[PDB]
Length: 187
Length: 187
Image (tube, rainbow over all chains, first blue to last red; front, side):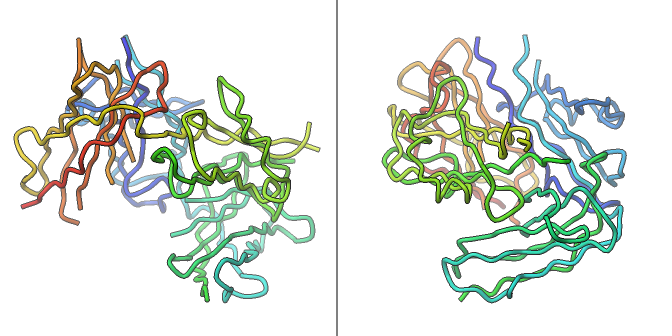
């Protein structure tokens, strides 16, 4: 027949601060069941610890996330369906926090673009920029562990709040503590 | 080095009524990278008409979307000094190809907070695929014929509007006209 690849998502989201709650949702449609979540590359042990009741409903809750929970996940149901697109679960708070700046400034004209700079006091091969949806960048040419991002066009009609993270690619799903919140003043 | 897989999204979204504009974004680290957008299973000619000015900024606009625009896209950046993995896929859907299905509450649009309700998507003509969208979407199956059943998890006050669609699995990104909006009422 036609078993549509299910939809996988995290609530409240996929980038969650260590110690905090989150619930992985897999839902193909109807009231139920044969949902099967698994982490890519290394079996995730908490999944096996989810009450069949929640699994038929496609709810895989994590009361208190830990670095061990991080990873790329996919789920399916069942004949079976294709695996859902990957959901990368991220935990933050593992390394010192970088600093986020807007060059030249947070104040920018409507429809314009601004360069956001993420600087780390300790070297890293990976940086992330999220808007309270993240962007992933490698370091930038001239900087001692700094990634620079380009955001725009900005518009007043929208909220432009950012935070950036530094991480080691050896474990791409464990990010540093978030940077202070950076608010863009569109004009 | 380390080449972080780019983030690929669409503005204003991945479900666009036929005739409307839509801009697919593929972004990464710097101000300009050699981004490359491509569709799966069938090459997308429209991507080649994109000026290099936009491409370097990772922008790939579609002024007026058509059936031929629907599809599974991914992108990456660099050159064979280093190209990144392809971004997570983005399924670009185009709606309004078929007669709209009817969407109903099973037993009713007014439910107790924390409760679950069954949504039914019915079509006057056979379709092997259905989709339910919260004004994201989860796709379902019938299932000998014509209807789809979706179960929406713990309903909470902290807004619930839905529209459903019908489609052919042999053309999974071309959806029908949307059913009327269905507002759920929490008590």
